[PDB]
Image (cartoon, chains in turn blue, cyan):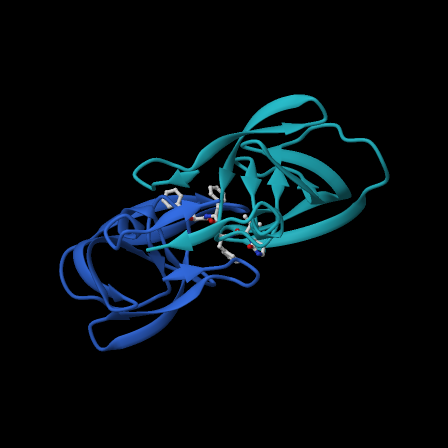
Length: 99
Length: 99
Ligand SMILES: CC(C)[C@@H](C(=O)N[C@@H](Cc1ccccc1)C[C@H](O)[C@H](Cc1ccccc1)NC(=O)[C@@H]1CN(c2ccccc2)C(=O)O1)N1CCCNC1=O
């Protein structure tokens, strides 16, 4: 598909039994999801955004389905206001910027 | 051009005769540049994202040439960690997400 940028490029993603709306975010290195209690091992991390840093939990090799496309990779979980689909997963589903 | 996302989508922009590197950011509503001098009246503004809120200066109707494509629009200036081209100007240069 082609997504214009007149509005936030929000799409439906699925992670396990949870469906959520998330930004397709070319300015995000990583995928940052709102608080959720995912299974398995994780490591603490600090990530920096526009106003400073937040603390997140890094989970590796998490399958996520984005608009019907399969992805699997690192997901950072923490107190973000918005779910962010970062470059690590955007490349997996074939996403490019075009103009 | 078509831009893939294995690297940060950083491009050269021209603003006030100065060349800067800036991030093409579909996850940004607004265009926000690191501290610099621009002419004209600005309006104090606050923006909030991951990590909290910062104070910026809003300049209107500022021309930026992004990768050879001309835009004229609102540019926020402030303590952003990185120069960011947001959706207000991405739409002007015909930028879309495709996969
Ligand atoms: C850039 C501003 C203008 C924007 C905004 O903060 N958008 C964010 C997503 C976001 C977050 C919170 C609120 C609203 C949007 C998403 C952006 O793509 C934003 C751009 C950016 C990049 C680097 C440093 C600072 C900012 N990205 C990010 O903030 C995160 C940070 N992050 C990360 C960084 C290091 C290590 C691991 C992960 C990542 O992958 O994306 N914004 C804030 C004001 C309101 N609207 C808006 O678009």
